[PDB]
Amino acid sequence: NTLAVQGCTGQHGPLATTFGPVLALMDNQNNSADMLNLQTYLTRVTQVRLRLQQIAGSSDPQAMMQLLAQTVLQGKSVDLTDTRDYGSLTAAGLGQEWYGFGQTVFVRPMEQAWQQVLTPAAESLNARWRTAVVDGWNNAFSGRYPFKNVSSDASLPLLAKYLNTDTGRIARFLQNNLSGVLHREGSRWVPDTINTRGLTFNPAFLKAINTLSEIADVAFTTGNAGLHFELRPGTAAGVMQTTLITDNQKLIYVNQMPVWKRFTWPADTEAPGASLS
Amino acid sequence: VVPGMFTRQAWEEAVLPSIDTVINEVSPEALRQRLTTRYFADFGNAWLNFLNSLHLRKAQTLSDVTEQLTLMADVRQSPLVALMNTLAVQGCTGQHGPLATTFGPVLALMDNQNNSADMLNLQTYLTRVTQVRLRLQQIAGSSDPQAMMQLLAQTV
Amino acid sequence: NTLAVQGCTGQHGPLATTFGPVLALMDNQNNSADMLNLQTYLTRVTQVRLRLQQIAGSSDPQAMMQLLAQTV
Image 1: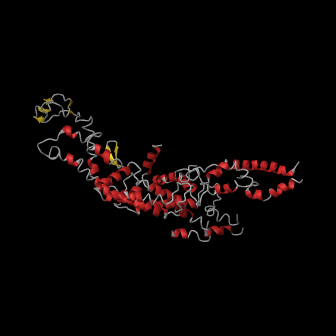
Image 2: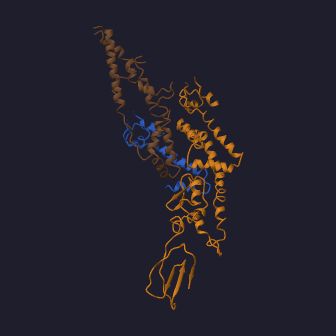
Image 3: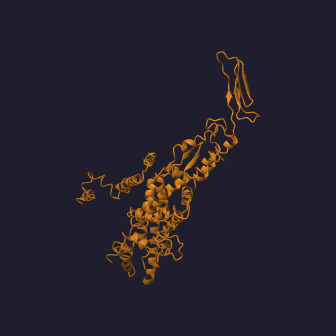
């Protein structure tokens, strides 16, 4: 208002080429009916605020905060990514002379919500990973060999439901919740370099599931537990015969010309075990 | 270059007296139509061969491209609103005008009166080309731009 | 600007070869000089300011500082 009263000094005015653009916003006469107009921004920014009142209370907002911040990192039209793409459109249209004012009031107070909507939603991926994978993993492989040095065994056809590369319950969690920030490049997972402004991974977590997708490419290649390694026996001072039995596959070596016995693991035999005599 | 001799100050001054020197020297007031429209048909035909001659400055390496689209779509300091301003002043010589069938369409762009409200209008091109420039500032810096450049050039 | 008006004393002038290249910058009558001028340069340095403004923004773990430097 007070900027409009001083764009008409003199007499349209003499300085109407310099206050020209900013007086062209607050017009709403819009004979084109598709101007930028600074209305249809204040009813664009207030339909962003009305989204952030549905969130912040009523109810369970960390759940809803991710579900906003998840659909900006992959898609569009939320609209917190659209008003910034409307607010910048006026500000770059002003003059490249009112830069610093157009950057202050048209793009900044929408961008300030984005840095505010991230760090709560980054917490909601922690409580949808300890209750979606870790409390399935620990519920079945707590205190089993080869995790903890005990007598019992982890269950192999249940192990291949977790660490696959296509349909495993780890690799089907990252393709649903981390669709923007995590790539399946090659065999490892890498952080996506775009869309990681202020969003850091725990550097043990990248070391974890680049290991669980490295066992997945050695042992669990075909979709189930199976690999083929070859043993060649050796000689030793004063041993007449060594017998290695794995899963009813023998290797009896009585110091003849050594060969290669192509084993497999785990074979579907009647008494799987290992023994050395 | 257009040779002069044609602009709005050359019509108001020194051809309207100058047509009156040769007509006294066949009914003259009927040739005053039969000479001006022969001049006006050669008025447009020296402008059309000026504007159709212009090419665009060969730019490269993505910063000169995004610096053109700043400078092309920036009111108060650009061509194409300073060019079409001076193109608007010479589409109204004579008196709508007599040559308004030849500068007709290019004056129909820079109107923004648009009683249909779906014209082509040359605004809604400079706020269309500047939402392409605004894409290429998100790319070219901030951040990791070779990654983002594929993700544009893949979906085209 | 002070250097601009002093390159036209006399009457383009008799001080041509001493203020040649420096007054070839601001002129915009250098229509074939590969355009090599002052005005693009100051906007060529305002975006190195703007990319450094974001590092002057958050820079929260001292990373995202080097994420603009990882491009270098």
